[PDB]
Image (spheres, helix red, strand yellow):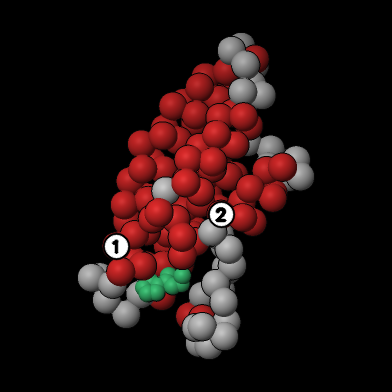
């Protein structure tokens, strides 16, 4: 029933993601000195520190908006990878599976709480 509960649930999931070794390449914005052509390929950079900062600033209205930004971290890695066998892309796929497994109940509970609110 709690329409605000998603925020702490997302904070806790972000904490789990930061402890995951698979999140290392994605914890901060991609370094343009390490990947000089990055912005030629990727239009909208995104990383987990930016997601956490947006959440903590009260700049997400719903968990769907947070989920769109986290999914952008993964689609950027898939677009930038030179190979479907690359180390960083392989880390993104495992981290995406972990994220999707945990965000599903957050989205469901929020949408159900919102439907109850507008009943
Ligand atoms: C973090 C920026 O780099 C990537 O996303 C990447 C690099 N190789 N495969 C994917």
Q: Quadrant of the C terminus?
A: top right
- How far apart are the two marked residues, 1 and 2, measured between alpha carbons? 17 Å
**SS of the residue under disc 2:** helix
- Asked if residue 36 is positioned above or below residue 45 in the image, the reply reads below
Q: Which mark is residue 48?
A: 2
30 relative position to 60: left or right: left
**SS of the residue under disc 1:** helix
- Asked if residue 33 is positioned above or below residue 58 in the image, the reply reads below
- Asked if residue 101 is positioned above or below residue 118 in the image, the reply reads below
Is any atom of residue 108 visible in this view? yes
Q: Position of residue 55 (x, y in %)?
A: 67, 43
Query: What residue is drawn where x is 30% and y is 69%?
Result: 87
Most extreme residue toward the right is: 57
The residue labelled by disc 1 is 90
Q: Position of residue 8 (x, y in %)?
A: 62, 29
Is any atom of residue 39 visible in this view? no
Q: Quadrant of the N terminus?
A: top right
Query: What residue is drawn where x is 51% and y is 75%?
Result: 42
Decide: few, some or many residues near mark 2? Use Cα within 10 Å; few <14, some 14-19, many ≥20. many
Most extreme residue toward the left is: 85
Query: What residue is drawn where x is 54% and y is 41%?
Result: 15
Kindly check if marks 1 and 2 are in contact, taking CB atoms under 8 A apart as contact: no
* Mark 2 Cβ inside 8 Å of ligand 1: no
- Asked if residue 82 is positioned above or below residue 11 in the image, the reply reads below
Q: Position of residue 80 (x, y in %)?
A: 41, 75
User: Quadrant of the rendered structure where residue 31 is?
Assistant: bottom right
Q: Relative to the observer, which residue lies in front, 20 or 43?
A: 20
Which quarter of the rendered image does ligand 1 occupy?
bottom left
Q: Relative to the observer, which residue lies in front, 12 or 59?
A: 12
């Amino acid at each position: 029933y709690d329409i605000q509960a998603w925020k702490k649930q997302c904070e806790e999931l972000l904490n789990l993601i930061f402890q995951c070794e698979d999140s290392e390449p994605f914890r901060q914005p991609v370094d343009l000195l390490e990947y000089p052509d990055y912005r030629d390929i990727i239009d909208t950079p995104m990383d987990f520190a930016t997601v956490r900062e947006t959440l903590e600033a009260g700049n997400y209205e719903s968990p769907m908006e947070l989920c769109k930004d986290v999914r952008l971290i993964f689609s950027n890695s898939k677009a930038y990878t030179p190979s479907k066998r690359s180390r960083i892309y392989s880390m993104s796929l495992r981290l995406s599976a972990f994220f999707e497994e945990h965000i599903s109940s957050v989205l469901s509970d929020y949408k159900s709480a919102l439907r109850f609110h507008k009943r």
